[PDB]
Image (spheres, coloured by chain):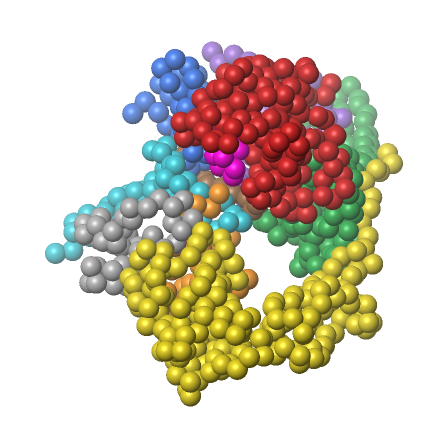
Amino acid sequence: GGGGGGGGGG
Amino acid sequence: FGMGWNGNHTELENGSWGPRFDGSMQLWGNVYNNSQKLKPYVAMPDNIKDFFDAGFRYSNSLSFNGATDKSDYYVSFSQISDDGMIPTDADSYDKYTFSARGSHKAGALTFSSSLNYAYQKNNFATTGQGLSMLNSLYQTPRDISIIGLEDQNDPFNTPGYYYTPYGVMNPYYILNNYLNEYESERFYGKFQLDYEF
Amino acid sequence: PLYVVDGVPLNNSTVYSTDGLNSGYDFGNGANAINPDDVANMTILKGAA
Amino acid sequence: NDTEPGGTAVEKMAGDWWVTVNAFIDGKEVEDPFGAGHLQMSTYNTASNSETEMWLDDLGNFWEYKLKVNVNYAARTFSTTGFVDNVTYESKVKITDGKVLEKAATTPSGMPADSIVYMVQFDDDEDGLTYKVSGFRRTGFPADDF
Amino acid sequence: GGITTIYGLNGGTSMYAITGMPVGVFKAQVAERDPQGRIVVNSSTGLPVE
Amino acid sequence: AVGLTGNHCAAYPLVSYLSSTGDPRIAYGISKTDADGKYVGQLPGGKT
Amino acid sequence: YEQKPESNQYNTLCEYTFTESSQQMDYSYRILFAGALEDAKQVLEKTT
Amino acid sequence: CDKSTDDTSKVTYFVTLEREGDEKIVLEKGQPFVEPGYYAEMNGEDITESVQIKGSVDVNTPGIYNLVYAAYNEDGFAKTFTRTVYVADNTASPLKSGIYTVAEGSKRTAPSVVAFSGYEIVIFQMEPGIFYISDFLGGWYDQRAGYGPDYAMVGKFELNDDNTITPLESYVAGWGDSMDQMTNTLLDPATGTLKWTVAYAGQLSFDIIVKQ
Amino acid sequence: NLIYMQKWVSLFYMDHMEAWSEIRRTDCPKLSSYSAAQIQASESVYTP
Ligand SMILES: [Ca+2]
Ligand SMILES: [Mg+2]
């Protein structure tokens, strides 16, 4: 499926 | 455990993979004008809980009524104004309605009518994975005082010297400086003609 | 379900963000506009036959 | 009404340690003969997650040894029965009189940390000595590092 | 095919409608297991293997 | 650069080669380290 | 290039730990075939 | 109702410390050591008088003397810098101490070749024949790629009357480590430069040369 | 090797999909025989 997301800083 | 990554201590993380809480005095946050904040390395278990306020909501509703053996009449008004528990006025909802409903019978004929107007003004504290309030809020070390970040006359809370630069921002900045408003106006109603024969 | 008020279909359109991942927000649905103090009776027809 | 995070069966005796290695020569204890200073080592549960054995891993910083030791979790003691195979390079190690002492040691920052102490012997040590590996649990503050 | 996305992240958890299954089936990354139930992990890091 | 933050750093094979050959193109799209001012590449998959 | 130490977007490309379900090129697959290749088919139908 | 997580922090005001003068100094036996100077600031007030210095320079005994300069915060936080002082042997020699600069023609040799120049190294004599060298590699790792002093090849060498140079000892901390072989070494007692090519970890070698 | 190694530098920050494919066709740059951990431990074994 579509949408994507980032990760975080660390 | 407090602020850090890889189990090691850090002065700038958005997370709590640091050492086990010591009580020792360690540094944290950015450096402003050759100065830095220094605090005991302890947990602040209420920090996220303390960030919230109490939402308040006040409502006023009126109605006017009457009838005869051939007619009836209803007219009402409602008002609602919510400023929820997230700080500032970003949780807002104002509802206003007005209604007027009548029916009159004259013989076999009945004509009635209802007309309603609705207003709303929503303001929303936007969510998401970027520079939003809650995402920025969850990404806090267990030892960092969140409500200590609201004072913008404290340079260390200004966006350029916020304690962590990892994809998040000072939550009180985001709520005080972003915008996501909605205003709506709405009219609906009906007309009915009944005739028995 | 189809909201029917007196008895005319009521608009029940929802206004919420189309990208819930980065700018999630929700601004209400069409039934939220009716004032509950005006309701005499509500009857929910569950079946579709 | 509070969630318990849990752990492996030997959680409190696993960990990272900053140890040094002394050696008993002529009956008197010699402070770090090999001059290796403070060395990192780890202990940690086995895949079986029993409460009667754990891994002792020097990380290759002294003799390059890593073996399973028997564990008395209640007493916080560990040892081997005789010499046990090493998993790192085909040797044998003997761990005697090991113990993990809660909050007993002191970090370089002057704070309480867990102490660890055990005696060790190696079947390829041509001098046949018995060494005393002692140290504390690593805090994670750079100031407590070496 | 007998499958169609209803909503779902790219290379992440996704909710489907699949032919002989209830509305809203979820698929998500689980770790590899040996034929005997045990969890496969990476020889060098220790972390699970997809 | 807009959708995400900066995620890419120089990799070790490219940096060691541009350094060995004296190539001045080592300055195009790559930036000296903000700490010592030299060119450093990261061994593939070796961040952690 | 490699994955910057302080962010985490491309760990699985660098460590070769993606899989088929990681969809690491579904966006491009759709662009090339349902974007470009279809438009091209239409072009060759419409002009001589 | 009442809130429980007020910020407990104290704002600590750090110290600034600036070294005035060279970092490495080479003096001859008997020549007095004069403090080059330093400046220390805290919140704009001058705290130069508060700097502590650990170490001493025995000008009448050849060797290496390290001095550590430090100034301290009110919360005990410190900034520091190091100054290293070297002492010669007094005895004459065509090799003069001590701060040398890697000259024009210094390069790799295996497997690549790359030109480097401009880097400083340190050479002083601790015995009428034996000299201490801070980096046989002319800074190919120390200050070329910035790997640090640990990646400098320290050692000793004993000047021959052929004016060739015979290596006594060499060691690179952090890799092992010592050189493989030493060849093409001699001193032109009028340049005044010293040449050497040194071979390293199995398949490396350089062709450096130094001058004041 | 010299034509291929410069083809590789040339395609940095220009056309990475091709760079990957020309690495695959010509297998130059060669894959080193040393591990990432062996290269990190002693740089001298690595051919830049
Ligand atoms: Ca509010
Ligand atoms: Mg298309």
In the rendered image, which quarter contains the N terminus of chain H?
Answer: top right
Say which of D121 and G30 sits in front.
D121
The residue most toward the right is H2
Residue drawn at x 29%, y 63% as measured from the top left: H110
Q: Main secondary structure of the magenta part?
A: loop
Q: Residue C43, located in which quarter of the rendered image? A: top right
What is the drawing colour of chain F? Answer: orange
What is the drawing colour of chain A? Answer: brown
The residue most toward the left is G48
Q: Is residue H49 magenta?
A: no
Q: Which chain is yellow?
A: H
Q: Is residue D57 magenta?
A: yes
Query: Magenta stretch?
Result: D56-65
Q: Which chain is purple?
A: C
Residue drawn at x 58%, y 75% as measured from the top left: H88
Position of B183 with respect to G21 (left or right) is right
Q: Is residue F20 above or below residue H36?
A: above
Q: Which chain is cyan?
A: G
Q: Position of residue E42 (x, y in %)?
A: 42, 30
What is the drawing colour of chain B? Answer: green
Q: Position of residue H114 (x, y in %)?
A: 34, 70
What is the drawing colour of chain E? Answer: blue
Position of D4 with respect to F5 (left or right) is right
Q: Note whether residue B197 is visible.
A: no
Q: Which chain is red?
A: D
Q: Note whether residue D30 is visible.
A: yes
Say which of B6 and D15 sits in front.
D15
Q: Is residue D65 above or below residue B117?
A: above
